[PDB]
Image (cartoon, rainbow over all chains, first blue to last red; front, top):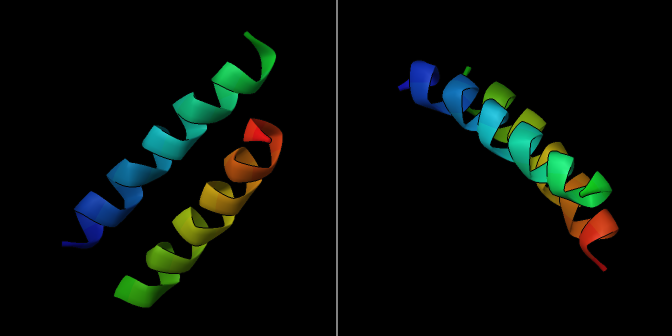
Length: 21
Length: 21
């Protein structure tokens, strides 16, 4: 399940991309 | 640890949440 926790990181990582756009 | 990542995401979740508003 740790693979899902780390995978979610990219989720919040992509969201931060919205901060700019 | 699951909480380990859960924490990281918890940080990015708050980070994006910040820029969000």
